[PDB]
Amino acid sequence: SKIRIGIVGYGNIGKGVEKAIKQNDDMELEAIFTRRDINKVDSNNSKLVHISRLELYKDTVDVMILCGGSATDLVEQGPMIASQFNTVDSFDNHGRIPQHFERMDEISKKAGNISLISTGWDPGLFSLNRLLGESILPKGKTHTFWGKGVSLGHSDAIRRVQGVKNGIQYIIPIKGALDKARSGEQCDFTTREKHEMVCYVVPEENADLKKIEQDIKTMPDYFADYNTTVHFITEEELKLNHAGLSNGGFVIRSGNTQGGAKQVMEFNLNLESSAEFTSSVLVAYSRAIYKLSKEGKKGAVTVLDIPFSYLSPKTPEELRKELL
Amino acid sequence: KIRIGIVGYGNIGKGVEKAIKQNDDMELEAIFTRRDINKVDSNNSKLVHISRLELYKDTVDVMILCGGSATDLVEQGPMIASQFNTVDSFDNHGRIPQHFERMDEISKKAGNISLISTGWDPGLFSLNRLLGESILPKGKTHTFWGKGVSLGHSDAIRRVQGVKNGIQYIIPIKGALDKARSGEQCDFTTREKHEMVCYVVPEENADLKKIEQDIKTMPDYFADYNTTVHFITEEELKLNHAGLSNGGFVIRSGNTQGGAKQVMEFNLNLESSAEFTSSVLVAYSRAIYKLSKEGKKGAVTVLDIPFSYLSPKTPEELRKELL
Ligand SMILES: CC(C)C[C@@H](N)C(=O)O
């Protein structure tokens, strides 16, 4: 009697979900729904099933994990899947979450299913800690930094600069800003003080390195506001040391108690593989959604509504005995 | 609007009183002391003798037990829970299963809800231990205790012979902390994570100080740690060791299929441990108030409470601001 999981999208995240499931004995992978012609994408990968056949699994999948491979799926179609299954997604457009919730709630609701939106680390785990922090320390500041990680957008930008063969960009929290937050001295940070950007560029033969550097550093919207460093490297080093699959970040609540005493709470992640971690979180929440659906819960939910006890396959007593 | 009653007025109780002031949606109804009426009327303030607890029925939504004493809670807890929704910070991990059972039985009878073992540990750290092993099933969880007093160990020493008053500190080892943070995965011994430093005021007859080294051999308390010992005057203990600060770390180091290193960390750096613990109790009282109005009865732990219940903001507001 294991939890039957369905995967939609076979990009890095779906690949990770399939992986995570192996680390979860109480779960089985029923199928991987893809758009690519399964016929040519091998056949020994017995779990692969074409997206056109999704509906045929309406009764064999307990939780459908949406790992949409960037397109219309990775934002629009989950609503179509919620109409048929209990789902879990990591919709990451913070500004549009209120709307995504509205829509998903209606569907999952009248369909009698349950849909979990925006889980992962941010949104997801960082969200939970932002809430915990301001809930426990009502008087204070909340600072979220996004650990060393790539920005697809900024990388494409770098590529539009004259004389740039190829390149990559990283956003990195500034240590000095972290140290001050970690100290109880409450304060607000300017954009320039929280994060710095680091680019590794492969120049064309003869290109005007100093020009490229400034073209990137003074680039409006993307870099103008941040201290940016440009390192020039070869195509070999680019491929070897900048796969760009890692990430991390910090959530810090710097506050004071009534008497004025300093109190600091911090939560952070260091991810060698950002995608595999997100997937692991997706799977864990799948366990929670399964329980919830069985309890007969309906509508859309966020990690903000789920007790941590639901993320574990252990019983209530085992937890209170082992972890409390 | 949430009417809070404080039971006990030590450091935590004082802390709850202050924290209530940081919550516009909450009101302090009274502070219950064990002190004899033989005080000074009430000395003004919100102080009320414990004997009058019964009288506040239907005028208190949540009783926050700031008694401070695991053993006292064993009996007093059920007592209160039979009359009010309660919130305590029962900190004896080893006996939490028993406390839950007792509090559960009672609270269900009276139709009330009792939240036990909240605080930073048990409480917040328990939450992260769970989150940690839930997201990274394959890995190792390590908990450290920042640098501060370890109350229990402070009494165990006060029970020693030639000692009449003393204090101890628990201190994480930078070396252990870094390894944990390296996603290297491994097992640590008690002696590898923390060292103990004691400060004791002896002399019950200038008593044998070297036999006071019967503290370093104390089973379950020291001996498992490199325990450094010092002796001082009780003036040098009040104006030098008002150990209010404390902190800790919960590190989950693990690997996802394929061996990629994944590290999660939660830590606290508290200038005033008690006050922090107090803010946690209040935040959770809000959650208990809500569950209460929803009709939940019986005992619960932080593991059963959705984080959204700790905030006075609405669900739509949280999704918009924090999600
Ligand atoms: C839209 C995202 C996939 C990439 C964007 N956050 C960026 O880094 O530009």
Image: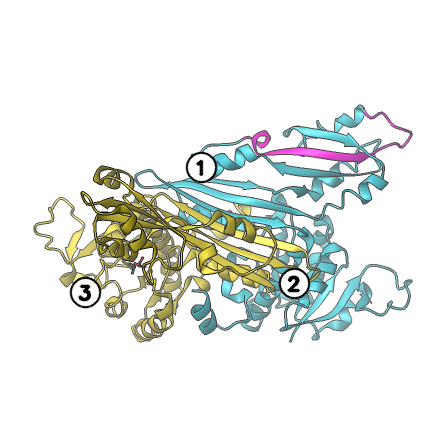
Chain colours: A yellow, B cyan
Q: Position of residue A30 (x, y in %)?
A: 23, 53
Q: Which mark is residue B6?
A: none
Q: Which residue is mark 3?
A: A55
Mark 3 residue element = helix
* Left or right side of A143 for B223: right
Q: Is residue A4 left or right of residue A323?
A: left
Could you tell me the amino acid type at mark 3? Glu
Mark 1–mark 2 distance (CA, rounded to whole Å) = 41 Å
Instruction: Establish whether ligand 1 lies closer than 8 Å to the Cβ of label 3.
Output: no
* Tag 3 subunit: A
The chain under label 1 reads: B
User: Which residue corresponds to mark 2?
Assistant: B86
Badge 2 element: strand
Range covered by the magenta-colored residues: B189-209
Q: Identify the chain of the residue marked 2, using the numbered disc in the image.
A: B
Q: Residue at x 52, y 71 (%)?
A: B313
- Residue A321: x and y in percent read 55, 46
Asked whether mark 1 lies closer than 8 Å to ligand 1, one says no
Judging depth in this view, the residue of B180 and B188 nearest the camera is B180
In the rendered view, does A167 fall on the left or right side of A97?
Answer: left
* Whole-number angstrom distance, CA of label 1 to CA of label 3: 45 Å
Of mark 1 and mark 2, the one earlier in the sequence is 2
Q: Amino acid at mark 2?
A: Thr
Q: Are marks 1 and 2 on the same chain?
A: yes
Q: Neighbour class for label 2 at 10 Å: few (<14), some, many (≥20)?
A: many
Residue with the mark numbered 1:
B182
Question: Which mark is in front, 1 or 3?
Answer: 1
Give the vertical position of A157 relative to B216 (above or below).
below
**Callout 1 amino acid:** Ser
Q: Label 1 crowding class (10 Å Cα cut-off): few <14, some 14-19, many 20+?
A: some
